[PDB]
Length: 158
Ligand SMILES: [Mg+2]
Ligand SMILES: [Mg+2]
Image 1: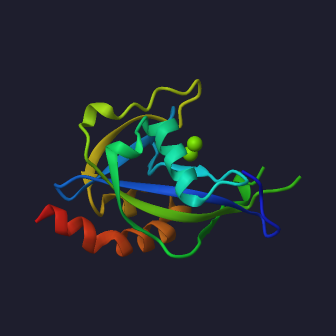
Image 2: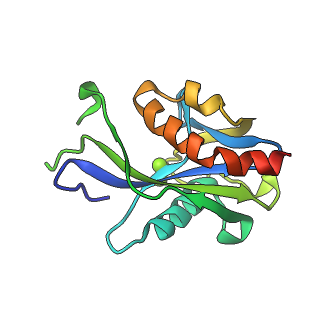
């Protein structure tokens, strides 16, 4: 997507949960680092539309396979380490986050449809596992996201 005048790229992130107090955790393509799905917002796209596009592209899912349970109100920002900053220059992402419950079967997820996948694949992890496990520069954002979505996911686990 197009970079704003502050160097931040508008971005959507996706936390997909089940009814067992678990969230979908995905392995970055060709790496041993893991994250939640995230993607850019195209010009003319709403955040929700961008979310469903990134859901289709890299998780293989339809609106019909999920239900939106929550979203974050404003932008959550992270800055890249100086080493990872590659005209115009992107220094980080400003993110809107969505909590989805997977209602279709696990077999509906397909992370291998792109010629260059974001992810190798995924597994279910315990709810709080992502906070300690994501790359450190995203940890502050992840902590806030997971805190905001906490009450909803724990209700399904009961
Ligand atoms: Mg992505
Ligand atoms: Mg993507």
